[PDB]
Length: 171
Length: 171
Image (cartoon, rainbow over all chains, first blue to last red; front, side):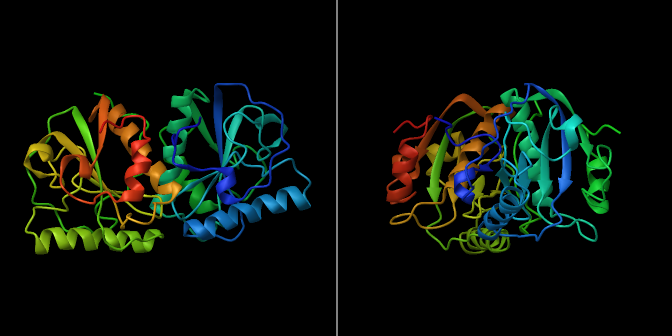
């Protein structure tokens, strides 16, 4: 099938995700990666983070009326990546101009007066490289924050700083 | 000479490992991977799994007199991989005819009547894919259960069947 691979991603069903209704595809290979924070509660164990992913999706689908959680990927302080829309489905995280050219990843928590643990940061970087190896991301993809993209206070000041120091980062 | 896209690994100093006294190196690329289980306590959070790794190393170093934790890598039920002796150092997990030609990875727990969670299995599998990309493991590496190379219950009855289904498995 999808033999347990690429990016140690927690599958949708494992975090009890509502089935998606999104159909819009993304054109492979994606050039951009936009990083953001949820401004929601944070979590530091697989159990609590799977519940947090369900909580974020519930808000997006039930209250905002979206086809699925808006991010392509969610990152938890448990150091695991959670499958959102994924690699081949357009997301709702960075406006009408980006959503079609990127993969959107978000850290579950508020990184205003906080910084995600090293394990969360490693998960993020594990995920992307996996994207390249699949052909979903261009080998020389560029990483942007949610400030460089849209009028926002996310991915959080302390997190924006770290992302800036990244090899594939583009001002 | 190939550094790419490969993985999240909780480094030694993050799980507060005693320094290693090991010096004997492995011959790249390694052909075999022996999967075992510690037959000790399991953990399902980063906090408790870092502690458990420290505990297994404690046992190996302090009680058995080895130069470091015997396994090259350890897998926690929190879904994270913990750096042991790593890809370049000979381990102590499968006896003298196998220790010098294999990478030993151990799941923290006892799997005679329990299976590791999907996230643990994914971490392990993605770790191996990483070994290959790194040139640390042969592209045609073979996975063996501890019991295939040594008289023991390890890696546990329930975990042994799962791995019997892995793509690179060879009894």
